[PDB]
Image 1 (cartoon, chains in turn green, orange):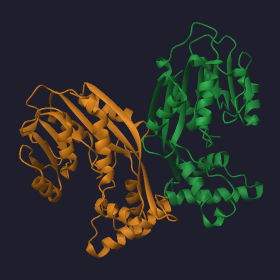
Image 2 (cartoon, rainbow over the protein chains, first blue to last red):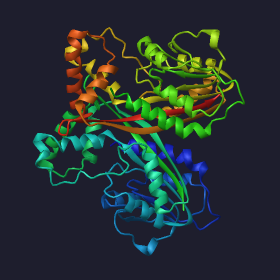
Image 3 (cartoon, chains in turn red, green):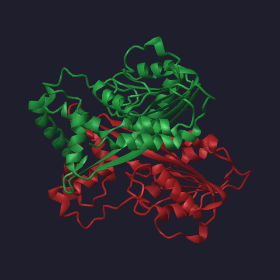
Length: 258
Length: 258
């Protein structure tokens, strides 16, 4: 049960960029996109040194984690189902003085739609702290499997999807241009090379199971991921000699103000 | 004959960081480590808006490129053979007001030795602009070949070599700590995700031929690189369907003052 690289990266990013924030005197509305487990939302709320007396909202499209997280998430802190790739409910447009979106490790289908939504969700002189992935072998891994002779045919009706910044040159320059085009007055964007080691293949497979973008079925799931694991060996993401997997990935860190 | 990704990255880095430099009024001594072709050294000299009347020094350990570069490099601009991994000639300690080292795409054996040498080469209140590689699939590629059952045995007496920042987390944080330990008063370090596309496998092979860290021989060279190319397909560095190779790499950009 390792969601660790999401947590570790969320926590290291928040702490590092906390002392670079500015808070309004009172009545602050804070939103966290792709909350999943409140482990991140709970440390965010403790770590944020300001008054949101009874206002910390957050969301996810998987309502299974949502309810478990909602069940553990107390009052003074409202949890709800929402995709940021869906058209905005104006109910909460210009609502939030601070919005967080730490990378969810699900491939995002539309980004400029999400950035505009983040821009609309933010109040007048609102602050945004987002992180997302510019390189991630997991994506390279599943994509390659979608292109094996065995699967290429049966997965042809699924969308690979394209990112205007993912595995491009100077993705920080691309995202900075896009966010100002959307109309953010302050924008600070940086690339951060990271590393996460799995010291057994069981831990790696369990991530790949959770992350798998392919639906398949209880019958074939076992087999599908056996092939992803064999692809991971060819790619040298898995060390066959030591039975380890090391992920080296790039992380774009966004600090912008309305 | 594609040294293009070295040139492109050198030029984009220099131009971007030119307006962030400070020049002394006159008698400036400038050094460029790993010059190779003067194409970079010649644009550096034109681009640097200061007086080095007859002082632009630069070096490389391959004296074949050196002489060709020396032959094309004019007077007022001295070229010579030197490794920065070799013990310093004190002849030129504290000599240089500005030193450049754009990444050479050869694996560096000792880094702290080189950084200390860069520190010793720099005058009082000297400025340093270095770039180097924190991730490069080419290195991942040759390393994996050194670990194939066919070659693992016959290449066992070669040194893989270790980097204290290469394919580590937050390599910018690692290098920044190291450069201050060496005693640089100003240090600004950033990661830059890049992308270089080869639109035919001939262009890719020709790079791999030039870059090959393995000596082999005229007899087996052909065969060695045939296997590297086959490894590159398994790794998905080469697209087998389109007959392209795309390199996604990380580039650490160092701006430091003595």
